Structures are given as C-alpha cells and as structure tokens.
Image (tube, coloured by chain):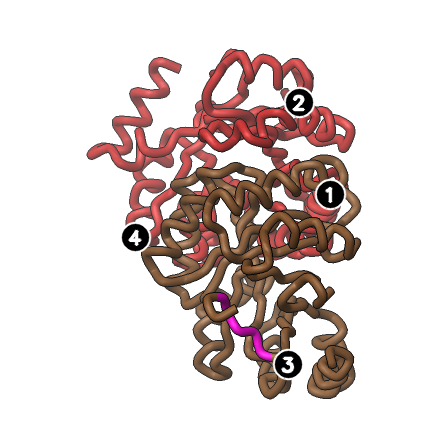
Chain colours: A red, B brown
C-alpha cells in the first residue's frame, strides 16, 4: 500500500543485543537485506539513546523503538517526543492503558511526522490473563483512533487473521505469517547466527 | 513495618523534569525533607541512565525507576537488570502482561537485592477501558507472587481502601491518602513551586 511504510524484503530485524559493539556489527552485516531495525529498552538503556542516531547515520535504516509505551497521556507524550527527537521513525505503544494514552502518542507523531504502532496482543504465557481477552477491543480502539500500524501476536496464525479482519486490508501489520502481516520480525535466527548475512538471505529465500 | 522500605517523611518526589540541570537542582533543594525520588523515562531517555548514579552519589537518595515495565519475561529481565545495574533501588512494573512477566522482574530483583513495585491501577481517563476492571485481579496476582510493594491509583480513596484490603496491612503501598498508603508521591506541587524546599516542608506539615 502506497501510504504505509515500505520494509525491505518484508523482514524487520529485532536487534535485541545489549552491547553497542555487537549490535552495530550485525546490523551492518545485514543492511543489504534489511532496511528496518527494531530496537528496545535493553539496548538503549545500556548504551544510550544516541545509539539510534548511530544506526541511522551508519546504515540508513529505519528505526522502530519497541518501547511498549504504557503510561498516562502526559508521560506518553514526553516519552514519544524524546524518542522521536533521538531519531526513531516509529514507536510501539500498548493499548491496555486506553484511548487517551494512545492518542497522546499519535499527537506527537503527527507533530513530528513519525509513526505509532499499536501493540494489540502478546504471545508469552502470561498474556492469557488480561491481554488475550482485550486484544480484539484494543484493535478496534486503534481503528477508532485512525491507527495505521499494528503489531500482532507471534504465535497462532488464526489470531493474525482475526486481527487483519478487524484492522482492514489497508493497515500495516507486523508480527514475530506473511499471508496476513505485511512484514515479519526476526531476532535470534539472525543476530545469533555465525553468519547473520547468510541467515537473512536464507529467510528471504523462503519468503 | 520493619521489612519494607522507610521513606523519609512518607513523601516521594516524582522528579518528572526532563533536563538534568533542573532535575538535580530541585532534588538537592529538598533532600533535607525527602530521601526517595521517583524517576521516569522522559528524564533517563533525555539525559542517560547515568543520571541515576548522579542522584545517588550527590544526594544519597533512594531511586525508584518508574519504567512501567510491560514486556515479555526475557525482555523484562533485561530491562530490570540494566536498570538495577545503573543503580535503581526499585522498579515499577505493570501487571497487565501477567504473572510470568512480573515474576521475571522479581527474579532479577531477588538476584540483585533490589525491589519490584507492582502497578495495580492508573487514574487517567483511559484507565476505565481495561485497567480499572483488571485492578483487583492484578493486586491478587501480586499477593500470589509474593509481591511486597505496590503502586495504587492517584484518585478515588475508596479504591485505595480496596487495594489495601487485598494486599494486607503488611505490604508497602505508595500512591499519588496516607490512611491507606504508606507514602505519597508528589510532583508538580514541589518541582514547579517557587521554592521547592518550602513546598516540601509545607506538605510535610499537613502530614502531621
């Protein structure tokens, strides 16, 4: 779709390593295959938010900040602003705290020309307690907030089809598959391999 | 209670300013009144996690990292480890991602001799959609995880009473009141006051 982001080869690298040296090396090695990198708090808290600018200046990749923003509106605004100021192209936000908390993020993204991804569901065991039962309503909330980017569950493809049904065929969906999601997120299979470059190439083949 | 933290004057400063210069100045000014400071992401993302060590080395205050940790277990473990390595005494964790996500934090806290606070509820308008209806079950989950520290809702004192009922009289409870909570969190009234020291002193007077 023309109005949503273009992720090279439909493959997003989850760069979950926590030391700067290792993180930069792997990302560079796969830049020929991947143009979009997701980074989270363990890396940025350990190495500093300046690492975002480094990924972009060294490799020219898009950066998605997987910060699972989950505060009150005013604090969400400030987290998003700081994250976008640091150079992130997009930020991942929880829906469980409700519509106003999500809208605060959307407001800053609108101001700064950046993107918000709504996290609709998670697939770790504890997700059954509260997250699973809220997922459809969170997705619908996103639709009613004009959200265009979503992060769906890692497991259970049939959950992915349900999500795709709620959000429509136009919205951008990423998941940790490609019959429903627009891009797949991959981590260990790439950044732990002895040859990250080869791993990415191989995954793209089957894709 | 002897087995939970002692917060000086039952008053925790929410240091929500985002520039290091302003943050440090205010905290120093109130150190005579407050020994426990809560820091969140806007400050640490803007200035670096090294700012935690600075608060502690300059002022010797306890630091609570209000990071509302809300990821899968493995990622929660890493966030907690990084935050404790930086010197935080405690970290605030969401309950809505479930018991395993909370336990991951408790595991690291146990390893490192630090504390986890479970956030049971929030009071901003959007909280009605999912958080309000999950609050009691999240508090009960905390009890069933051996959680000793809780953060409750800012408004509705009767909600604080319900929370205190679930967690028992022993557990440590903080809230943004002191008939149910062990300590109160205060932000703007202090850090956006003409003289922070006087504001802190005045609030403390209200508290007997």
Same-subunit check for callouts 4 and 1: no
Q: Residue at x 59, y 41 (%)?
A: B138
The answer to which of marks 3 and 1 sits earlier in the sequence is 3
Would you name the residue on which mark 4 appears? A21
Subunit that carries the residue with mark 4: A
Q: Residue at x 64, y 68 (%)?
A: B183
- Visible residue check, residue A6: no
Q: CA distance from mark 2 to mark 3?
A: 44 Å
**What secondary structure characterizes most of the magenta part?**
loop
Same-subunit check for callouts 2 and 1: no
Are the two marked residues, 2 and 1, in contact with CB atoms closer than 8 angstroms?
A: no
Residue B133 lies, in percent from the top left, at: 71, 36
Category of crowding for the residue at label 1, using alpha-carbon neighbours closer than 10 angstroms: few (below 14), some (14–19), many (at least 20): many
Q: Does A155 appear above or below B187?
A: above
Left or right for A102, reference B57:
right
Are the two marked residues, 4 and 1, in contact with CB atoms closer than 8 angstroms?
A: no
Category of crowding for the residue at label 3, using alpha-carbon neighbours closer than 10 angstroms: few (below 14), some (14–19), many (at least 20): many
- Visible residue check, residue A96: yes
Q: Residue furthest left?
A: A194
Are the two marked residues, 4 and 2, in contact with CB atoms closer than 8 angstroms?
A: no
Would you name the residue on which mark 3 appears? B26
Q: Which residues are magenta?
A: B4-8
Q: Does B56 appear above or below A3?
A: below
Same-subunit check for callouts 3 and 1: yes
Would you name the residue on which mark 1 appears? B127
């Amino acid at each position: 779709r023309v109005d949503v982001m273009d992720v090279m080869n439909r493959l997003i690298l989850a760069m979950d390593l926590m030391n700067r040296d290792d993180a930069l090396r792997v990302t560079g090695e796969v830049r020929e295959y991947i143009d979009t990198v997701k980074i989270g708090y363990p890396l940025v808290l350990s190495e500093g938010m300046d690492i975002i600018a480094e990924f972009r200046k060294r490799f020219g990749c898009r950066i998605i900040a997987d910060f699972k923003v989950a505060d009150i509106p005013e604090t969400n605004e400030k987290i998003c602003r700081a994250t976008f100021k640091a150079g992130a192209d997009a930020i991942i936000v929880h829906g469980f705290p409700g519509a106003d908390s999500v809208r605060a993020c959307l407001n800053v993204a609108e101001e700064m020309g950046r993107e918000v991804f709504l996290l609709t569901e998670m697939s770790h065991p504890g997700a059954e307690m509260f997250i699973q039962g809220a997922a459809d309503e969170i997705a619908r909330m996103g639709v009613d907030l004009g959200v265009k980017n979503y992060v769906g569950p890692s497991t259970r493809p049939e959950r992915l089809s349900r999500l795709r049904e709620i959000i429509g065929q136009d919205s951008f969906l990423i998941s940790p598959t490609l019959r429903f999601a627009d891009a797949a997120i991959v981590g260990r299979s790439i950044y732990l391999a002895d040859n990250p470059a080869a791993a990415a190439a191989g995954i793209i083949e089957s894709i």
